[PDB]
Image 1 (cartoon, rainbow, N blue to C red):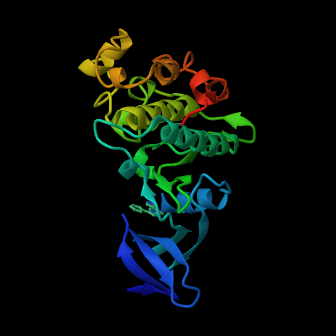
Image 2: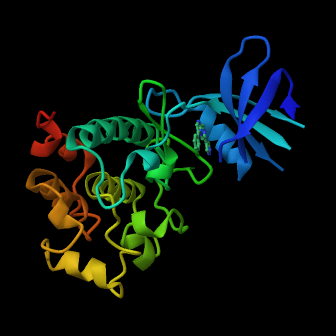
Length: 251
Ligand SMILES: c1ccc(-c2cnc3cnc(-c4cn[nH]c4)cn23)cc1
């Protein structure tokens, strides 16, 4: 099947890979039959660590998005192992870039996870899929988020325990969990709730258990600052930049 000039070559995720018969350019195609908001949000985005939005056309609705040859960051993680520290650090820098940007235009992704961090040919990281995204700052006014979403393992504690919560710390939490899985190749908990055994152990600082033992002490220190239950004591992105591991030379 094809749309306009573009031919849908293969299924990517629905999302197909589209190649132009004429220009031979490859793009990502989103086929939908909250979409309006996603299209609106995509237009507002212009960063090198965020998937490009080319435009949309209704028929089924069609979102035209940058194609990342690399695929998911998820594939680059090795189970129980993770990826080499220099690699994870670079990836984590590009994620901070993309997320800083969104935050500065009042946008929160709300679903950060390795499945939604795509890699281009140069292996540059792109924040992907704004179907769950929303505005948390408009006209210089911040709006707290009440709706629950994202993926349990990457979700912040306040979101399960609070009527309303700030958007930004939630994206920082998710970024920590993503850091953890890059360095450890496994996720700490099914969910951040106290009922879960793994979360409680972390709260008590039982670092000896997995996956913390697999992680070096510099990054582990950063994660001690990121996975802080108090959304208000949690470290901010501006502070993550000053983190020693973040600025440590690697490779
Ligand atoms: C596996 C391999 C490549 C991919 C892949 C490559 N390029 C893109 C662009 N967008 C998406 C996407 C997905 N949802 N919303 C947008 C996926 N992509 C995706 C999965």
